[PDB]
Image (spheres, helix red, strand yellow):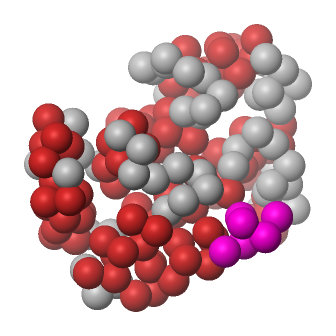
Amino acid sequence: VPSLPFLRHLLEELDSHEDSLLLFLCHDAAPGCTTVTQALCSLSQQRKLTLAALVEMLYVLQRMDLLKSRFGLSKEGAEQLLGTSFLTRYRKLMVCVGEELDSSELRALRLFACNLNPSLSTALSESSRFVELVLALENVGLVSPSSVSVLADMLRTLRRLDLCQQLVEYEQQEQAR
């Protein structure tokens, strides 16, 4: 619904970390994209870039300033649109969990992944974000939208039982659906 020029101008407001989170959220629906511009272009082509999808993206990114200025929506107004677009519970959860981790925790998790599978060393680095670790694990088949127990196990080893529980709960919910 919203025009591409409008959406793009909106993008200039995101920093590099937010761009990476958005590209991760668009990983299934905009295959092969390396820039947010490309991903939005792709969603436009598919009629997937709706008001609801944009609001959900901004909500997940905690950009309540942009929800107000571009859509006239408070946090609660935005919560009324969640779950009504192509965005999935799996990818939104991964972004949210990643924002609950500090740099030391992220380093530990990357080490756990490489100890579990040494081949991941070439896909990760000291600068890899949580969503990049998630994709690295997905790419070798260790996690997927239906199975996140390997990551829950890593969070449990980290002693972040709160984050582990979010992933165990998600997997149980997804399986029952």
Is residue 49 rendered to the left or right of residue 164?
A: right
Tell me: residue 49, above or below residue 14: above
Q: Which residues are magenta?
A: 172-177
**Going 72% across and 72% down the picture, which residue do you hit?**
173
Residue closest to the eye, 55 or 124 = 124
**Residue positioned 40% across, 88% down in the render:** 161
Q: Quadrant of the N terminus?
A: top right
Examine the image and state in which quarter residue 92 appears: bottom right
Residue 77 in view: no
* Residue 37 spot, x, y in % from top left: 54, 17
Query: Which quadrant holds residue 39?
Result: top right
Q: Is residue 68 visible?
A: yes
Q: Is residue 127 magenta?
A: no
In the rendered image, the vertical position of residue 161 relative to residue 23, given as above or below? below
Figure label count: 0
117 relative to 103, above or below: above
Counting from the top left corner in percent of width and height, residue 144 is at: 53, 50
Pinpoint residue 63: horizontal percent, then vertical percent.
58, 53
Q: Main secondary structure of the magenta part?
A: helix
Left or right: residue 63 compared with residue 12: right
Residue 20 sits in quarter: top left
Q: Is residue 11 shown left or right of residue 103? A: right
Figure check: 102 above or below 67: below
Position of the C terminus by quadrant: bottom right
Q: Residue at x 84, y 20 (%)?
A: 47
Out of 114 and 68, give the one closest to the viewer: 114
Residue 124 x %, y %: 19, 42
The residue at 45%/86% (across/down) is 162
